[PDB]
Amino acid sequence: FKDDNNIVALTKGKLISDVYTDKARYYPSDKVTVKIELNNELQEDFRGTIYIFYKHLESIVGKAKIQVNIKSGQKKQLNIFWEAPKDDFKGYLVEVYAVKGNKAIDNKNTAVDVSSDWSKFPRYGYIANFPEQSKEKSALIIEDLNKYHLNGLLFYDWQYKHNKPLAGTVENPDPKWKDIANRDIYGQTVKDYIELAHSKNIMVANYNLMYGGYFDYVKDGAKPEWGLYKDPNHEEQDNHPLPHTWATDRLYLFNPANKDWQNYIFNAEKDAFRVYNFDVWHVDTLGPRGMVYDYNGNPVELSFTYADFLNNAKNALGKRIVCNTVNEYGLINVASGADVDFLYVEIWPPARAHYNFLKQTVDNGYNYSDGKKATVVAAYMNYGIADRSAEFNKHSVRLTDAAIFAAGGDHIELGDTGMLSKEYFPSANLKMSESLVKAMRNYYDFLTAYENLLRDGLKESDNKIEIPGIEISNNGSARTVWTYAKQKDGYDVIHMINLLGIEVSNWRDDLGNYSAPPIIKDFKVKYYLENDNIKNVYLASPDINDGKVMKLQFKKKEDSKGKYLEISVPELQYWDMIFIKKL
Amino acid sequence: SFKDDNNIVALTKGKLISDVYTDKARYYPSDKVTVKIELNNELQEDFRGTIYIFYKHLESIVGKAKIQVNIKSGQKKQLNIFWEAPKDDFKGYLVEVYAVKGNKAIDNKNTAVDVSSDWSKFPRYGYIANFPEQSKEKSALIIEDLNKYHLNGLLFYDWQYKHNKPLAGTVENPDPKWKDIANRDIYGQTVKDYIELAHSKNIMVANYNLMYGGYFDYVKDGAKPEWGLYKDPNHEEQDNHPLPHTWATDRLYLFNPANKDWQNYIFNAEKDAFRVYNFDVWHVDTLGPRGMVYDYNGNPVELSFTYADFLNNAKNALGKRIVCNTVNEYGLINVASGADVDFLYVEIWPPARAHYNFLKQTVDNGYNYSDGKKATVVAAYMNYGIADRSAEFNKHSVRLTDAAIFAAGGDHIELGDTGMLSKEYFPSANLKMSESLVKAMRNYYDFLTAYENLLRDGLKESDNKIEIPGIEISNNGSARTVWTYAKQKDGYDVIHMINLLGIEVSNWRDDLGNYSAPPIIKDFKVKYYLENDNIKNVYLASPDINDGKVMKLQFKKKEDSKGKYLEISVPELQYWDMIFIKKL
Ligand SMILES: [K+]
C-alpha cells in the first residue's frame, strides 16, 4: 500500500483512536494481544483493511492484515494476537495502518517488550493514593498506566509506620489506617492494585526508608541504642522533621549497620510482605546526614553501611530490593556491592541542574556497576512551580526524557496522579496537558521499542561527530545540538538532542516556560569511522511518526580529518536517534 | 661511574647533604637554573670528595656536572651550581645530587625543575594566610621555605579590607594597615613584600575574595539591596553567611552575580585593589549551593549558571587572570565549559565526597568538562576532625591523599606560610607537620614537578586490563585494595598503584588522624594486558623510593586466556608507585 504522510496527516486520528497491549512486559513465546480501538470520525463509512507490522529495529519480524468495515460514527475494538519471539530481552515497535483502496489513511503505533525480568529495562512508575474505591476503578487506573508499558510501580506512602509498616497483625490485618501524612489508606485498594498490576506482569514495590522510626518508636519495641546520632555522646538522635499536621513530629533515624535494627525492621517488613503481595522493597534514604555516630560514639560512614543492609534485607525477606541513593550518595557502594535489581538516583535541587547530569548520573551507574545494572533517575520536572495550580511544560518534559532515555536511563515520573512535580509523590498541583500526554505515550513507546539500542550492550564511542553549520556539544550546552555516539555489536548509535532554543542548560525549567525547539530540516551529519562495514543508516524519533524507522541517504566521504559517513537527516525537533547497521 | 648502593647511602643518608633546592619555582625555556646544595658535615670526620649532579627527564640523563669539595667535620657550606634549562616548554626534570668518597656514594638528595612559560598547565598552588608587621628579611625566609616545594602560585587568603571594598584607603593614599574579615591586623607592606619576593621566584600571586559578598554596612559603601540575592521571592530575607560576632561583620550579605550593577561595583573595587597591590590573579571564591534563591524582583536565579558570565566579565574588566572555587563541584561544568579561568579549583567535602574515588573523579570531571583544556586543583583539608586540637597531621593519610590527587593528574592546595591546611579557615594552624611528614612532602612535591609530563600532560584513560596476582585491587579507591589504573600518551603508558590495603573505610580525610602505615608489598607481579608488543622498556618511579629516582624493571611478555600481557616485576610498593612503559 501507499504509506504517505501527505494524506495520513489529513485524516490522522480520525479512524484509529488508540493502540496498546494487554500487558507491560512479556515472557519469550507469550501470547501478545494488541488492542486496537477504532472510532470512525471520517464522516463516511470505512470499508478497508487494517495492517499490522511487528518491527525489531529496522526489520519486519511479523505482519498481519484484517478486513474491517466500520460505519461513520461507529466504534469497534479489534484484537490482534502475536506470539512473542523466543529471544529474551528484546523490544519491538508495532505499527498499525488503516488502508482504503491502496492508500494509508490512518496510523498509530505501540511497543512490545519481551523481557523475562524487569531489571534489565526498568520502566518505573508510581501509585501515590489509596482511597476507598472499587476494583473496577482501580483496574481503569492500572489500564491507563499500562498504556505506557510501565513494568514496575512504586507504592508511595501506603504503609502504616516506617518502623511498623503493617497496620494490625498478620493474623488480622487492619483494613484502614493513617499514613505518615495522616491520609486514610485502605488495605483493599492496596491489594486490588497489586492483583491488577500482577495480571499485567507489573512488579509492585513497597516504599519505606532504610532507617526511620516514629516519635513513639520505644512503644513499638525499637531502642535508642540502635539509633544514629548527630554527636558522639548520644545527645541528639538524627531526625527528619515533618509538618505538624502529620502522624509524627519527626522521623528518628537508625544505624543501618546495627544488627538489632536490621532484625527489627526485617521482621516488621516480613509481616507487611506476608499480607500485601509486594515483589520489591524500595529502600529510600535521605542522603548525606553530616557527621553521624552510633549510640556508643563510633563514627558511622553512612554510605558504607548500605550494601550490607540491602543484601541482608534481600536474604531475610526473599524479595527484590531497590535503593534510592539520593544525589548519588552511596551509589558507588550500592552499584559495586549490593544485589539490587537496578540503581535509582533521586536528584534533590538546586545542585545537578545542568542537562549533562541527566546523562552523567546514568554513566556513573553504568561505570560503578561495571555495566551490570541499569539506572532509574527521579528528576522532578518544573519543581519551581510545584506549589502553584499549574501545568507541566510539554517542551522541557520532552527534553528531560530525551536526555535520560538517550543516555540509557529510565525516568520515574508517571503514576496514578499524572506526573511527579516534587519529592512528596502525592502532591499533584501540576497537571499534564492533553498534548503532553500524547508526547509521553510516544516517548514511552520509544523507550520500550528501542531498548536494545538505548541500554543493551553499549559502550561510549570515540568517533568524531560534526553537524556542519549547527553548533554542537557533547554535554548538553545551551544553544547547541547535544550529540554523542555509542557502539554495540552490529550497530553504532548517534543521538541528537535539540537545545538550540535553550538559553540556560537547566533541565528543571523552574518557571515551566520553555518553548518548542527550532526545527532543523534536511541537514547533514558527519560521522567519522575507520571501518568500511556499513550495511545501512536509519533514524527513529518519538517526534516523527511515533518512532517509525526511516532509512537515510548517506555517502562515504573523506576530508582533512579522515573518512566519514555524510548522513542526510530529514528533520530534528526534540530528539533523533540515528543508527548505523554493520554488515 | 661510581658505586651507588642504597645499603651504603642509607648508613650516612642525610649526614652530608642537608638540602638541595633551586632559586625559582618555575623557569622559562633556556633560563639559567641555580641549583643550591647545602652541606653540613655530620659524618664525624673531614670529607674530601666529589659532589655529582645529574639532570634527568623521566628515564633519560639530559645533563651532568661535578664539583670537588673539602668540608671539615661540623662545617656547613652552600654550593651554587648553574644549569641551562632546555628549550622545550612545559617539561619537568629530576635533579639527583650524590656525595661520593673514593668510588662510593655516601649521601644523596634530589630536587626537581619545572620549565614552564605559564603556571596554568601544571599549577602547584599554595597559600599565605598571615600578614603581620614583619621585616622583608623574615618574609624572604618564608618565601624561600615555600619555594622548596616548587609552589608556582600563592593564594593570599584574608589579606583584603572588606569583601565589597578590598582596598583600605585610596589608590593615591592606601592605608598601611587595616582589619581583615576576622578583625586581624593586616600590614600592607608585608603584602607588598611577599608579592615582590614571590615574583622574584616566578610565583603567581592570587587575591582572595568572594564573588558576591558585602559587609553588614554595604549601603554606606554604595552597594544596594536591589542587587542582592534573596532566599524568598518577595525580597524579605537577603541571603547571607553568618560569621562569629568578634569578626568585622555579623554576616556577609550575598549579591546576585548576574546583576550588572553588582558586577560594575565589585569590578571597580577590585580594580583599585589591583592598582595598589601587584596581584596577578583574582581568586574568586563561592560558598556552593544556597537552596532556592531569587533576585530582588522575585525572579528565580540558579547561581551555578551565573558564574561563567561573571568571571569572563571580571577578566575583561580587570585585565587579570581568574580562578574560581566551585565548591563541591557546584558550578564546575559551567566554569569548565564556559569560563576563561586559568585552571579549575574544587573544594570538596565529606561526608558526600569522602570516598577516595572523589579525589580522582573531581579531576576527571574538570578534565572532561573542559574538553581536556584545563588542569584541576583540589582543596581537601586533611584531618579536619582533630583540627581544633594542638596536634600533628597524620603522615600516612596525608601521603595517600596526595598520591590519589597527584596520580589522577591533579594538584592539592595544602602548603603555605602556616605549614599545612587543616580547615577551610586558612589561618587556623592547630595541626603541625612532623619532621617525617615534611620530608615526605618535599619528596612528593619534587615528584609532582619532575613527573608532570607523565601525570598531567597529553594523557587519556586506558582500557587495558591490569591484574596484581594475589592482591585485592580496585579502579576506584576501595578500602582494602591496591587502587590501580592506567593511562596512555604519545610514547608512554602509565600505571598507578596506590596502596589502600591498610584502609578499613574509603575516606580520604582521616578525621581522627589515626590511619596507619600501609603494608609494604615486595617483589610482586603486575600483569598489564597490551595488544601491541612495541615495548622499549619498563620503569618505575615513586616518591617513597630513593626520593623519586627512576628504576628499570624486569618484565616478560606472556599470554593467557585474557590475552597478551607484560608481567612486570615490582620491587616494592609502600604508598604510591608509578610504572611507566616506554613505547617504540
Ligand atoms: K599611605
Image (cartoon, coloured by chain):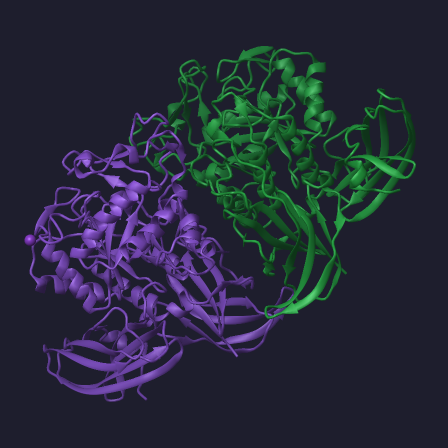
Chain colours: A green, B purple
How many numbered tags mark residues here?
A: 0
Q: Position of residue A97 (x, y in %)?
A: 83, 36
Q: Is residue B415 above or below residue A22?
A: below
In the figure, is residue B75 to the left or right of A246?
left
Q: Nearer the viewer, residue B442 or B347?
A: B347
Give percent across and percent down for residue B18. Answer: 18, 73
Please indicate, yes or no, whether residue A160 appears anywhere in the rendered image. Answer: yes
The residue lying toward the viewer, choosing from B322 and A318, is B322
Report which quarter residue A275 is drawn in: top right
Relative placement, left or right, of B86 versus B561 is left
Q: Eyeballing the image, is B286 above or below B235?
A: below
Quadrant where the image shows the N terminus of chain B: bottom left
Above or below, B469 against B339 in this view is below
Which quarter of the picture shows residue A526?
bottom right
Residue B63 shown left or right of residue A444 in the figure: left
Q: In this picture, is B173 found above or below A126? A: below
Res. A266 in view: no
Q: Position of residue A396 (x, y in %)?
A: 55, 36
User: What residue is shown at x 65% (from left), y 12% (from top)?
Assistant: A133
Residue B561, percent across and down? 65, 65
